[PDB]
Every structure is written in structure tokens, then in C-alpha cells.
Image (tube, grey):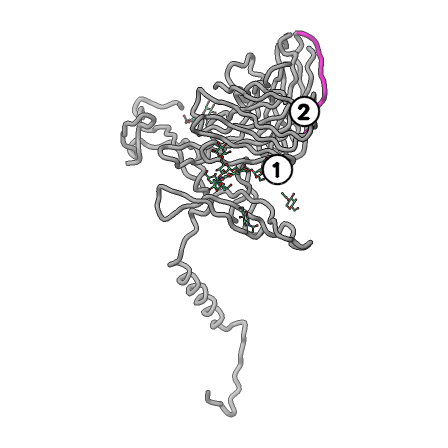
Amino acid sequence: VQLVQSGAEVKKPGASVKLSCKASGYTFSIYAITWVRQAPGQGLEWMGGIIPLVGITNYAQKFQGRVTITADTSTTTAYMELSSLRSEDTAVYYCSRGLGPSIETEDDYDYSYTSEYNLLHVWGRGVLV
Amino acid sequence: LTQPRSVSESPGQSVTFSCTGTSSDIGGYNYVSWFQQHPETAPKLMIYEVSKRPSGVSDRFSGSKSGNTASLTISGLQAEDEADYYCSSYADSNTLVFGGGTRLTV
Amino acid sequence: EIHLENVTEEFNMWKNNMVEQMHEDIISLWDQSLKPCVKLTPLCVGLQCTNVTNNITDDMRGELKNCSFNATTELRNKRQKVYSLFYRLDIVPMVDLWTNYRLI
Amino acid sequence: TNNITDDMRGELKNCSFNATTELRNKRQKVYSLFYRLDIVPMVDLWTNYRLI
Ligand SMILES: *[C@@H]1O[C@H](CO)[C@@H](O)[C@H](O[C@@H]2O[C@H](CO)[C@@H](O[C@@H]3O[C@H](CO[C@H]4O[C@H](CO[C@H]5O[C@H](CO)[C@@H](O)[C@H](O)[C@@H]5O)[C@@H](O)[C@H](O[C@H]5O[C@H](CO)[C@@H](O)[C@H](O)[C@@H]5O)[C@@H]4O)[C@@H](O)[C@H](O[C@H]4O[C@H](CO)[C@@H](O)[C@H](O)[C@@H]4O[C@H]4O[C@H](CO)[C@@H](O)[C@H](O)[C@@H]4O)[C@@H]3O)[C@H](O)[C@H]2NC(C)=O)[C@H]1NC(C)=O
Ligand SMILES: *[C@@H]1O[C@H](CO)[C@@H](O[C@@H]2O[C@H](CO)[C@@H](O)[C@H](O)[C@H]2NC(C)=O)[C@H](O)[C@H]1NC(C)=O
Ligand SMILES: *[C@@H]1O[C@H](CO)[C@@H](O)[C@H](O)[C@H]1NC(C)=O
Ligand SMILES: *[C@@H]1O[C@H](CO)[C@@H](O)[C@H](O)[C@H]1NC(C)=O
């Protein structure tokens, strides 16, 4: 249940960033990893998420062309690429883990979903970008 | 999804608060989550879906839901609960939404 | 066809059992033709559907979706990805976070 | 967990298992009462019985 963030640089207009969320302490491939934006002193906004093994995303309607969440199951690291941020929506970005497995491989890679809609647990620390 | 911006009450007095919305956000699906975010730290998951709790949470922070409004009661309010309480839920078009955050001053 | 002179016959098209027999025969023939065919049981999976990126006229907005669904393969230990274009009438929204629609 | 007599001890079991759904890639946890005569012991890490 260890989520270690990397990348906390505030950039000038025109910039794009790639942030990473290293994970350990649990079976990486079967738990969902999601991203939440703090917003500059405002409420939370959902950005999207991924299931590492399958590699499936559900980017929100406002981020459906900007954010690019990926995952690497060999290094157990989740990544998020943010294009065309400019200077708007400067915020602390957080990485979260699912409460339970989303998929559930018995053996081999027969994933089988488990209808878990509580994908915001072990809420790791954030990075200010 | 919206919620009151702040609530106070007093130390030792149990405090209740709620978030509201339509049938596609709170009314159906029965997946309403609440988070307690202390300043300069990650939000902690508290209620799971309606009326549950991730272990390690003192006095359960049990909540309830009625109609399109979901709410929680903090029994035995202490100074340690001076935190921003966020409401979140599954919304249609297969998305998640969050409220604006309720500031509890105790 | 033999014409019957000086014969009057009382007809009733709503008491004619030839329609009931034709109905039953067409149902049975249709079911027998459909039975020895490919079943789509493995395709009842969640789909990620988005809007069609071609030039859509005002009346066709929302009528077609570009859906993606992992499926099965000749072997049983592998899978595949199958982008396909569906009509909105053929799919229904589902409650999920990763997939959007199911086949009706 | 209900109240039973001595004669019915072990006769009825509360058995949980992962059943399929209409969707091919979405299982569902279930819990069902079975009569002991309808199940047979089968030892595994997470299971105790299977259907006879
Ligand atoms: C069935 O099972 C499959 C088993 O894996 C599963 O993958 C599949 O469905 C998956 O569905 C998700 C969506 O839910 C797809 O996610 C898109 O991924 C795009 C990235 O693809 C690239 O990376 C994939 C994995 O990353 C590896 O590589 C990176 C390298 O950087 C590394 O960092 C990681 O650790 C991983 O090693 C990889 O699988 C992809 O390869 C596929 O595609 C290539 C061709 O590209 C093909 O040759 C390969 O054979 C293979 O099929 C590929 O390398 C990502 O860009 C997408 O997001 C874009 O599009 C969405 C659309 O809305 C936008 O919202 C995003 O913003 C973004 O576009 C924007 O990006 C720019 C940068 O920000 C913007 O500037 C600009 O605006 C763009 O518009 C998606 O996240 C996933 O790929 C897909 N998997 C596969 C294999 O196809 C399952 N299907 C179903 C229906 O369940
Ligand atoms: C059979 O077992 C199931 C659990 O697998 C029991 O269901 C639980 O029952 C308790 C009773 O206090 C509830 O608090 C739980 O919420 C129930 N869980 C679920 C998932 O339903 C069930 O009651 C058992 N039945 C019998 C007759 O013993
Ligand atoms: C659907 O999206 C895929 C993505 O590669 C594309 O290749 C395909 O042509 C699209 N189909 C339609 C009908 O737009
Ligand atoms: C697709 O079209 C529907 C039609 O109403 C619209 O509501 C939806 O936002 C569109 N989505 C995209 C990604 O263009």
C-alpha cells in the first residue's frame, strides 16, 4: 500500500508534463490506479484511471483529449501525461488505488471484472504542478 | 453535485452534514463516497459506499442516504476533525464527480 | 385449376386455418434455419463506445457508435481487440467505470 | 448461523462461490445454502466442497 509520487515541477505556458506514481506492497496488475486533481484551492476533479494488466481507461469528459494515463506492469509504475496545460488549473495531482481488485485473474490472464466502484482508497500523497 | 461550504457546531457536539444532487448522481446506484482531507495531506476514505467504513476509523463515521441527498453524522466530535469533508459519487456517462468540500471548524 | 360452374361457396378469411399453419410453418422454418449457426455468446461483453469520427449529418448524430471490445479467438488461451461500428439501437448503456455499453 | 437441533448438525451448509453473469468477463460472489448430501468434500487453499 505504498504509492510514491514523482514529478512536481510548475512549468511556463505551453508546457506539458509526465508524472509517475510508483506502487508497491500489493499485486500491481489487478488493482485500478486513478488520478485526482486538487484544483487551485477548489474541490476535487476526477481525471481518469487505468487497470494495469488490461490497460483500459475512462478519461473524464473534460480531459477526454488531454490526459494520457498509462501503466507499466514490469516496473509497477503508473504514468500520466498532461498535454497543453499552459498556466491554467495549477494544482496538486494525486494518485489513488482501488479498494479491491477490479479484475481478478484466477490463473493465467483470464481477468474477470468484479464490479468494484470504490476506486479511491490508499490515497497517496500529491505533487504540485 | 454540491454541498454546503462550511459547518461549525462546537467541540463535543455531534455534527451532521449532507450533499445533494439528482437521481443520476446520488439517488440511484447506491455508490456515494465521503472523504476527510486534512490540510497539506491526502484525503482519507471514510464511508466507502453508503454506511460502511475502511478499518482504522474511530466511531465508524456512519452515514445515510435518503432521496437524492446523502449525509453523515460525526458522533463525539473532537478537535482532530477540523478537516475538509468532500462528497463524491458515481455519475452517469460512466464518470465520477466530487462536491465542493465542506469545511468543519468544530 | 378447375373452374366450378354453378357452385356458390361461403368463405371466411378470419376462420381460415391456412394462416395459422403458414404462421407456425414460418416460425419452425426460421428457427430450424437459425439453429445450426454461430452463437454470439462470447460477444456479450462490455464495450468502450465513442462517437464516429466521420462527417455526420444533423439527423445521424448519436445513431452510430465506434465501439471496441475484446473478444475470443480460435484458441482458448488468447484474446483479441475488435473495433466495430454499431447502431445506437443495437447497444444499451451499462453501469460501469471502464466500459460504456452492452449489446442489446 | 440459524438455530438448529442436534439431529441436523452438519446437514445444511452455507457455501459461497464465484458464479458467472450475463457478461463473459464479470464474475459475481454468491452465497447459497446447500444440503450436505448435495456437496462432496474437496480440499483446496480457498475451497472445501464441490457439487456431488
Ligand atoms: C482489450 O485488452 C487490451 C489488453 O491490453 C487493452 O489494452 C484494450 O484497450 C485499451 O484501451 C485503452 C483505453 O481504455 C487504450 O488506452 C489508450 O492508450 C494510448 C497509449 O497507447 C500506447 O501505450 C499503450 C500502453 O503503454 C505502453 O507504452 C508506453 C509508451 O510510452 C509506456 O509508457 C507504458 O508503460 C506501456 O508500456 C500500448 O498498449 C499502445 O500500443 C497499442 O497501440 C499501438 C498504436 O498506438 C499499436 O501499434 C499497438 O499494437 C497497440 O495496439 C501504445 O503504445 C493512449 O494514447 C490513449 O489515450 C489517447 O487517446 C484518448 C482518446 O480519448 C485521449 O483521451 C488521450 O488524451 C490520448 O490521446 C491524446 O494524447 C496526446 C498526449 O496527451 C494528446 O496531445 C492528444 O490530444 C491525443 O488526443 C488511451 O489511453 C489502450 O491503448 C488499449 N490497449 C490496446 C492494446 O489497444 C482492451 N480493449 C477493450 C475494449 O477493453
Ligand atoms: C450465509 O453466509 C452469508 C455470508 O456469506 C451471510 O450473509 C451475511 O450475513 C450477515 C448476518 O449478520 C450480514 O451482516 C452480512 O452483511 C451478510 N453478508 C452478505 C454478503 O450477504 C448469510 O447471512 C449466511 N446465512 C445463514 C443462514 O447463515
Ligand atoms: C474506430 O476507431 C478506430 C481506432 O483506431 C479506427 O481505426 C476506426 O476506423 C474507427 N471506426 C470508425 C467507424 O470511425
Ligand atoms: C457524441 O454525441 C453525443 C450526441 O448527443 C454527445 O452528447 C456526446 O457528447 C458526443 N461525444 C463526443 C466525444 O463527441
User: Would you say residue B62 is visible in this rendering?
Assistant: no
Q: What is the magenta segment's predominant secondary structure?
A: loop
- What span is in magenta? B1-11
- Near mark 2 (Cα within 10 A), the count class, few <14, some 14-19 or many ≥20, is some
Classify A68 as above or below B9.
below
Residue D43 is left or right of residue C18, and the answer is left
Alpha-carbon span between mark 2 and mark 1: 18 Å
Name the secondary structure under disc 2: loop
Residue visible at 54% across and 42% down?
A: C48
- Near mark 1 (Cα within 10 A), the count class, few <14, some 14-19 or many ≥20, is few
- Label 1 is placed on what type of residue? Gln
Percent coordinates x, y for residue C79 in the rendering: 41, 43
Quadrant where the image shows the N terminus of chain B:
top right
Residue visible at 47% across and 71% down?
A: C17
Q: Chain of mark 1?
A: A
Q: Chain of mark 2?
A: A
Quadrant where the image shows the C terminus of chain B:
top right
Percent coordinates x, y for residue C102 in the rendering: 52, 45
Relative to the observer, which residue lies in front, C95 or A62?
Answer: A62
Same subunit, labels 2 and 1: the answer reads: yes
Q: Which mark is residue A90?
A: 2
Residue at mark 1: A64
Say which of marks 2 and 1 sits in front: 2
